[PDB]
Amino acid sequence: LPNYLVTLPARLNFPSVQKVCLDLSPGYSDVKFTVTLETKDKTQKLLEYSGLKKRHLHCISFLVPPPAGGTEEVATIRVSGVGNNISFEEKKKVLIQRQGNGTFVQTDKPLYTPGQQVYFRIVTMDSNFVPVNDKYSMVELQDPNSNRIAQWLEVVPEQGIVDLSFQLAPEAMLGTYTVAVAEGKTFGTFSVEEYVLPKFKVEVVEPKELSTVQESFLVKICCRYTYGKPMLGAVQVSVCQKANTYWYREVEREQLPDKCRNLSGQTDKTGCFSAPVDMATFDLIGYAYSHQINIVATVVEEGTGVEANATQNIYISPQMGSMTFEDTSNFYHPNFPFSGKIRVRGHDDSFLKNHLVFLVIYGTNGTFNQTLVTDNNGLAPFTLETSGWNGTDVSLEGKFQMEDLVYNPEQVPRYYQNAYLHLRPFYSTTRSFLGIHRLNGPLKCGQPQEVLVDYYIDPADASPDQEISFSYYLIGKGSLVMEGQKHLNSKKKGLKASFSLSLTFTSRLAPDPSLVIYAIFPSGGVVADKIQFSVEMCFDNQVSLGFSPSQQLPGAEVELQLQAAPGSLCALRAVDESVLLLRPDRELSNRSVYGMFPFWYGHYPYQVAEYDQCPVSGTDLFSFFRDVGLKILSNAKIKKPVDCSHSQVRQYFPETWLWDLFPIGNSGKEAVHVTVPDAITEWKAMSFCTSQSRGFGLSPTVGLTAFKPFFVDLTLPYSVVRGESFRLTATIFNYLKDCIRVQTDLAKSHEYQLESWADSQTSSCLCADDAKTHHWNITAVKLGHINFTISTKILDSNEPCGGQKGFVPQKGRSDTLIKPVLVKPEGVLVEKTHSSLLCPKGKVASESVSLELPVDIVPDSTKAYVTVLGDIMGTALQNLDGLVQMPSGCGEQNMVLFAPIIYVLQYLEKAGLLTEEIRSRAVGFLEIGYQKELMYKHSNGSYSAFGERDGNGNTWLTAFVTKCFGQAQKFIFIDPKNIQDALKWMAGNQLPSGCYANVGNLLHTAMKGGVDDEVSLTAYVTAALLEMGKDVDDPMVSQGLRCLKNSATSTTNLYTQALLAYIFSLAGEMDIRNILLKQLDQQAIISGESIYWSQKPTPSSNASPWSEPAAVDVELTAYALLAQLTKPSLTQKEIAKATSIVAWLAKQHNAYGGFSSTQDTVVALQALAKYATTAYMPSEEINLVVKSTENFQRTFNIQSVNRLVFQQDTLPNVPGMYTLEASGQGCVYVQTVLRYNILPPTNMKTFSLSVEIGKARCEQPTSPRSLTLTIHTSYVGSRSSSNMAIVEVKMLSGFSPMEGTNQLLLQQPLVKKVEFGTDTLNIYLDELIKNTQTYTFTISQSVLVTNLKPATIKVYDYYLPDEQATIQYSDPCE
Ligand SMILES: *[C@@H]1O[C@H](CO)[C@@H](O[C@@H]2O[C@H](CO)[C@@H](O[C@@H]3O[C@H](CO)[C@@H](O)[C@H](O)[C@@H]3O)[C@H](O)[C@H]2NC(C)=O)[C@H](O)[C@H]1NC(C)=O
Ligand SMILES: *[C@@H]1O[C@H](CO)[C@@H](O[C@@H]2O[C@H](CO)[C@@H](O[C@@H]3O[C@H](CO)[C@@H](O)[C@H](O)[C@@H]3O)[C@H](O)[C@H]2NC(C)=O)[C@H](O)[C@H]1NC(C)=O
Ligand SMILES: *[C@@H]1O[C@H](CO)[C@@H](O[C@@H]2O[C@H](CO)[C@@H](O[C@@H]3O[C@H](CO)[C@@H](O)[C@H](O)[C@@H]3O)[C@H](O)[C@H]2NC(C)=O)[C@H](O)[C@H]1NC(C)=O
Ligand SMILES: *[C@@H]1O[C@H](CO)[C@@H](O[C@@H]2O[C@H](CO)[C@@H](O[C@@H]3O[C@H](CO)[C@@H](O)[C@H](O)[C@@H]3O)[C@H](O)[C@H]2NC(C)=O)[C@H](O)[C@H]1NC(C)=O
Ligand SMILES: *[C@@H]1O[C@H](CO)[C@@H](O)[C@H](O)[C@H]1NC(C)=O
Ligand SMILES: *[C@@H]1O[C@H](CO)[C@@H](O)[C@H](O)[C@H]1NC(C)=O
């Protein structure tokens, strides 16, 4: 009878196109076939084909119909063949399933410091490696507290690629961040910590995984600096084996002592110490000790005493070798030779060449032995004659050695990993053979490959005149790739010959494709073979990367050759090799891209898995197609009839070098020139590109070696004082093989004095892996930043440098390093500010400033300038990042750089002056503020002044922060979970009377501005809510307002009156606003035309022209000015009263648009924003006249175009009298700023301040000097307790706080946060009482500076700069 064979994949993908094949044996000229696909919605007639007079295999392709269930659906494949007298039908079940899309997220590094800009990319592709260009609903970024800190909505890719960036905050939240795409369904993570710290690295070079067969192993501990030069010092080693912890507990049993072997010694001139450690010390065998050796190496530097450690754990493994079966199947053909290979490896996986290995054959006819020898690739080929096997199962085992190893049973056994193979005979009803040659190695993709096919045809299955049709099949990834038929006429080649197949491996073919070849004889029998290949993981878009040249000096040019398909867009990544080495994670690799998709599935899915229905009552041709994911319908004898009776510590993470997108032109190649970085390290680079024509591509990881012959290092102090001598330490390092003559020149300048003088000139000779140190005594002369230029260069010297001539390379002859050092003047800088509001109403408006100088002025510190702007807010606009020159490290003090930006933008938007250049600058500032604040978020959602270092949230600061994040949603993104969880916690702390409890107090009495009771807070929380736009019908407002009505009846405090007047100006109860505003007028102090309020007693009448900002008065005056400006329609008499209040608040400014502290700088600029929003006028032309005594004059111009422009000019004239003269129409804000240095006055009016100095060993001149400071302070001021306190400890020149100075102070009383600065240590104290407090820490000297000038210890109330104290301290050995 004639046969048929229908095949199609068992798993059909809805985006993919699949094939269904039909293999017809001859004899169907009257029988018509129709292969239909029967689903739920339709019956799709796939293939419709009648038979021929010969054997003809006819495949078709078709589009997969949509699965009905949205995700997947089981359908029915039906094959029917209707003829004259023949009618038969057959069905199978198949699985249609939606394709998975695999999305990846690549960050430029996987570890960042805070303040670095994080760049990342997002591309979605399908299993055909085609980039998806659909829009994404939401890309958001999450911080370690899982607060949503940025989002981009409706991002459209460019050729499938999304390129995004985010600026980290310079102290941003430490930990693991999360990048979410498409509602959290696909994501990636990256880390942020502080690093780059170590000066040198202790490296354990020789430690590697050990084996119990070693008698001793050599521990090699090499110590080299971070730039690579060796370091001399003493080494101590601790090579221990700890006792294995055991779960069982028994009385009077102790853990065994750690078997150790301690070693000590010194490094050689390579920086390495080495000593063998015998394995007899450690119990290599007992369960009572752990199987790991722990090596602790601690190295103290020769001379300086700098200590560093290293820990490497070494697991011990007894395994000595492995063996695997490659190029073999799990089946065989009887009577014909079965070939294979045996791969043999040692304990380190090296290919063991010419190794005698034993192949043992287990069978029914006896145990037979063959000896094999391996080749240079570690492969041992064999061939077994299956004619003597009688068609039975044979179990194969490859052994290293024949006799079994004899070991003591208590001892840990070393074993050899044998290879095993179970062979089932292929059931054939024919006596023929079909056997396929297999190819060696992972095959190169795209190249045509010739595969040889051996065959024998027994004459009892087919006549020797009959033409023989072999049909072959090629499967990749569980789908049909290639098909064909090889016809062989048995007269031309005989009945024993071979043929070849010309195959080409593409990317759509799997990394493991399957070739199945079969032929049906007229008896219905089948003979087949199945072989799987190893292909390189390729892509249809060839992307290459290349550097030209691949080695270059730092600072020079280099050509970056980038190649892809035409029309491709490429995403470059150039990274320090240390970054790819320290986390070899899922960085983008060919294995990672294939790893996204389940390509390993090549079996029937369980929804359409074909089981053998056995009546349970209490390797053939079908098994080949199931093993490649192919369903099969056939009537030939294809199946066996069913029988039923049952990281590391290697290096730093510096700059991401290159991160750009490059489009590839029509040429297919693109070359750009990039400048090589100054750092001496090797750069690894990779590129990935997308094209709609060729799909995704990926490059090889190519390198660029930035190498310079010699490196120089500058050890310089940061800041020194005038009159001091410091030690400039310059070291010169040689990385070459040869000795070079080097001459190091210190550039002569008039800005410092050299004590070396003419002794500095020489030319010392420096050989290989060698270093020469150069020092200069430098007396500090000029004040300011002084550049120190050192030019070290290689000479063409003929003197004996090394024995032969001194080497001169042709590139890298002269290295020049320039490092500046600040020479700060003595004492403390003082600032004085006379800010003026001149509104020329057509007339000439005039004011006069007198620059009076004190007597004991530190020289050259005198500078003064004048700032002119067309806007009263404009001084704060230029210094939004620098409003207050104070530490901003608490929960509230950070908000001095968040709140004022929001009111400025609301003013500039409502006045329309908001440019995109300004909006882009400002928006980025708020993002840096938002991140710092979230470090003070608690887990419940509230905020405190120091985060979780406080026990609870603070009621007032949470209401203040919530006020700002809601109004920030109009400009930048804010997570609503932060707003809602702050409101959820504050609603819980609302008291029954509608007032708010002061959890964490109402803050300090000059911070808050007031204290009297809890009603004072009920004022602010309701005020903040209404600022946010909340309703009067809001439950937190309405119950809040109900508590504020009976307590507005008999209220006495001046602050509380001005605060309440703001609230009822927002609440709309004008009846109570006017009662409180009139109580303000009777307390108003009018000085000239200025109207302000003050809780402090009235001065005589004299207000100093220079700013003396009472933070009580400044904050208080704005809350009145705010209460005035919330009447929705303003009279010209109310505008003028607001104008009269303004003429005092604008005078108290500092040099940066700030005032004196946190809230007052916020509240007053918040008020002046509401005034400038109300009183905005585009100024026509204001012409300002500046006059001085000694022939100095200056004219500025202010129009509506430069209203916001910061215009500044310094006064060349010595301090005298100056005259403003404002003419035009508009208003011009003019500020006068004076600076000088005086000696710090020992003022002890509000705080007691003293300093004890602990005993340093002055008689030790080669010890890193330690000074132990003991500081005493107390609040002797008028009130009971102070506010939050700063202890500002300026350092001595060349000193630094020791390791653990943070952790020392935090345990000591009242300390909340310790902060080390550049040259100043700031300590936060909660408050200071009248009890003398004592705080002690130790500082050490890192750079020698002599003739030490005194540094300044300063203690001051943060929210009251007027309540301060200042002392000095000096070196006791000087
Ligand atoms: C893998 O990615 C593809 C490509 O984006 C996803 O297919 C797309 O899914 C969307 C949403 O279901 C389809 O848009 C819709 O079009 C219909 C008309 O057919 C319209 O009535 C809807 O309102 C909607 O706009 C889009 O056509 C479809 N694209 C293709 C080529 O079919 C697919 O869902 C992703 N698969 C997975 C598992 O994520
Ligand atoms: C290698 O050297 C480093 C640096 O000397 C060692 O790290 C240090 O370990 C000590 C002891 O645990 C830490 O001090 C402790 O800090 C906690 C708070 O963090 C405090 O409550 C304790 O009272 C104590 O002072 C110290 O912070 C830590 N330093 C750093 C920079 O991590 C490290 O343990 C050494 N490793 C080996 C194997 O020798
Ligand atoms: C993933 O891609 C990497 C490239 O980043 C592939 O690395 C390749 O590794 C092989 C094996 O070392 C190298 O193949 C050799 O090529 C020479 C001809 O240049 C040939 O004579 C040798 O017999 C050998 O086949 C190859 O140079 C290297 N690079 C590239 C670009 O192919 C890696 O194989 C890929 N991995 C997978 C699983 O596909
Ligand atoms: C101390 O040395 C540094 C060099 O390390 C000096 O800074 C340099 O100042 C010059 C000014 O002529 C800069 O040249 C120009 O800079 C501008 C601004 O970016 C640029 O548009 C020009 O194309 C040109 O390159 C030079 O780049 C700059 N170098 C650095 C690294 O900032 C500094 O002025 C010296 N200070 C003293 C007190 O000696
Ligand atoms: C530099 O010269 C000054 C002169 O007073 C001396 O005191 C100091 O010790 C010298 N330092 C070095 C490193 O030579
Ligand atoms: C958070 O607030 C709740 C009250 O809602 C309080 O019980 C809890 O102790 C607070 N936790 C912290 C860490 O502030």
Image: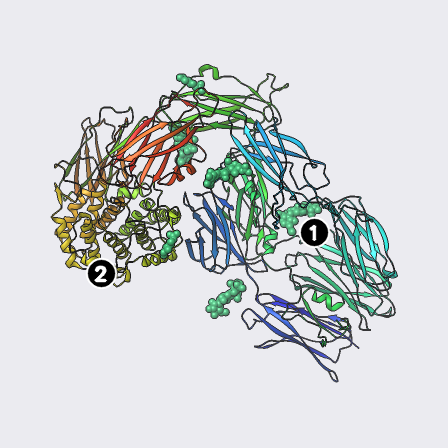
Q: Is residue 481 left or right of residue 142?
A: right
Please, what secondary structure does the residue beneath circle 2 have? helix
Q: Position of residue 839 (x, y in %)?
A: 17, 43
Q: Say if mark 2 contacts mark 1, CB within 8 Å.
A: no
From what the image shows, is residue 270 above or below residue 139?
A: above
- Which residue was labeled with disc 2? 1042
How is the protein colored in the picture?
A: rainbow
Amino acid type of the residue tagged 2 in the rendering: Arg
Q: Which residue is mark 1?
A: 442
Callout 1 crowding tier (Cα within 10 Å): few <14, some 14–19, many ≥20: few
User: Is any part of residue 589 visible from this angle?
Assistant: yes
User: Which x, y percent locates residue 807?
Assistant: 60, 23
What is the distance, in whole Å, between disc 2 and disc 1 at their CAs?
A: 81 Å
Give the secondary structure at mark 1: loop
Callout 2 environment at 10 Å: few (<14), some (14 to 19), or many (20+)?
A: few
Relative to 601, does residue 1372 appear above or below in the rendering? above
Please, what is the three-letter code of the amino acid marked with disc 1?
A: Pro
Q: In the current view of this chain or complex, which residue is farthest to the front? A: 252
* Label disc, if present, on residue 1300 of the rendered structure: none
Question: Does any atom of ligand 3 lie closer than 8 Å to the CB of label 1?
Answer: yes
- Farthest residue, direction top: 758
